[PDB]
Image: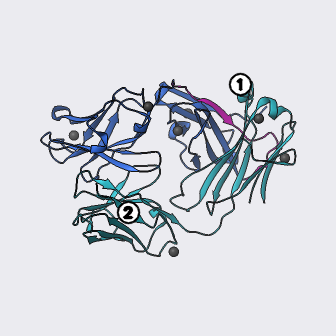
Chain colours: A blue, B cyan
Amino acid sequence: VQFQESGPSLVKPSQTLSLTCSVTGDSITSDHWSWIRKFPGNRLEYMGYVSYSGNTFYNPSLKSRISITRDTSKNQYYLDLNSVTTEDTATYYCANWDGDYWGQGTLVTVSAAKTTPPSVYPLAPGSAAQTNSMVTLGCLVKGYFPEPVTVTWNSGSLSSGVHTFPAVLQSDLYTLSSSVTVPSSTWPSQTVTCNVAHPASSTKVDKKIVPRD
Amino acid sequence: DIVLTQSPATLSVTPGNSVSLSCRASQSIGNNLHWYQQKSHESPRLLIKYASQSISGIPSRFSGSGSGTDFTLSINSVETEDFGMYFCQQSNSWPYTFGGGTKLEIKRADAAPTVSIFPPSSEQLTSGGASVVCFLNNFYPKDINVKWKIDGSERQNGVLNSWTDQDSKDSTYSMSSTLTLTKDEYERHNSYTCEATPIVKSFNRNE
Ligand SMILES: [Cl-]
Ligand SMILES: [Cl-]
Ligand SMILES: [Cl-]
Ligand SMILES: [Cl-]
Ligand SMILES: [Cl-]
Ligand SMILES: [Cl-]
Ligand SMILES: [Cl-]
């Protein structure tokens, strides 16, 4: 069983947050279908569910701003949350009733601020760094809004020895780095590229890590 | 609304040992209690339903008990993959409510970090930014001390640290430490050092 959650990652204050969950490997007309959100502090909140027959239950904390509808012919269901505020900034998940199946989160940011794509800087070792059996390369991702970015190395074909660090907020913009460790003998002979995707600005940047001049 | 109180807030355990996590409900919820495991990355995994029923494909070392107001999740013979957040949820009374979570850390032998320092990229220096990045990889325990020095002198201003989650295989942490300067400040100094508490990496801007 799988969920595809779709819709904006950035919403303006007072507007409507609309998300869609596409369900595969289960019919919408059996079981119950839920929306759950996780706040930046780690607090989980059950927002509502819709039953096999179209019946809805909503968390009273949302005070009638919430609507959940379904379309049985498409195996899809919907969340409409009206009059959003910065308090609605959270990771939204679609799940079945008991949460046996629980989609990947979607981070939604409520903000008046403009989307800013990231600047990506390759981090090759210092000209005179000590050599070893392994070399660590990095990729600095600076000045983006909102979260998230997804970082991959060689479009995901280099997955071992990768550490991607959580983003930090500096002056209303996000920054993070990613490190990759490969065998010394293999670089620069077998190239290493970071790939940074920013869904909010519909942008992807690839930077090859090149030895320094 | 039913309030679910989880304890302890944090627990460290050595692999092969047991843990018992507590969930207490503000009013009776019968047996309508779920337990979940969430890594700080992915989505929660359901471990236990109806307080004590095993889910298809969950290892047998996970078991739950309780009815009414007091519940426990036990992990006998904990594995390195068992790290992460454990949450209870009550489905007896609408709205369904979650506990605050217990963070489980896996204990292992002390491990020194591998330290790598990176001067600002030539591309960054053109935009008037100068980030000096230091990676401290595969260490334990989590609470490492990172000192920056510029031309010999201790430096705290403009330093930000960020940790990965525990590694699911070897139970280590990694962290980035970034010294953000302006190009102006960067070009007025020669030597830059990050040190883990001492494991030291250094470079000279003029080299
Ligand atoms: Cl289907
Ligand atoms: Cl607002
Ligand atoms: Cl991010
Ligand atoms: Cl690539
Ligand atoms: Cl222990
Ligand atoms: Cl500065
Ligand atoms: Cl120094």
Please report the residue visible at 62 percent of the width from the left and 38 percent of the height from the top: A192
Report whether B177 appears left or right of A100.
right
The circle on residue B85 is: none
The extreme left residue here reads A53
Please report the residue visible at 51 percent of the width from the left and 35 percent of the height from the top: A149
Q: Nearer the viewer, residue A160 or A166?
A: A166
How far across and how far down the image is residue B21, in percent? 40, 69
Which part of the image, by quadrant, shows the N terminus of chain B? bottom left
Secondary structure of the residue carrying numbered label 2: strand
Q: Magenta region's main secondary structure?
A: loop
Please report the residue visible at 58 percent of the width from the left and 48 percent of the height from the top: A163
**Other-residue count near label 1 (Cα within 10 Å), few / some / many at <14 / 14–19 / ≥20:** few
Residue position marked by numbered label 2 in the rendering: B5
Q: Quadrant of residue A212?
A: top right
Amino acid type assigned to the residue bearing label 2 in the image:
Thr
Q: In which quarter of the image is ligand 2?
A: top left
Please report the residue visible at 18 percent of the width from the left and 48 percent of the height from the top: A31
- What chain does mark 1 sit on? B
**Magenta residues, as a range?**
A115-132
**Other-residue count near label 2 (Cα within 10 Å), few / some / many at <14 / 14–19 / ≥20:** some
Which part of the image, by quadrant, shows the C terminus of chain B? top right
Q: Quadrant of residue A86?
A: top left
Residue B100 visible in the current orientation: yes
Secondary structure of the residue carrying numbered label 1: loop
How far across and how far down the image is residue B178, in percent? 69, 43
| Gap between marks 1 and 2 measured at Cα | 50 Å
Amino acid type assigned to the residue bearing label 1 in the image:
Ser
Residue position marked by numbered label 1 in the rendering: B127
Q: Nearer the viewer, residue A200 or B119?
A: A200
Label 1 lies in ligand 6 vicinity (Cβ under 8 Å): no
- What chain does mark 2 sit on? B
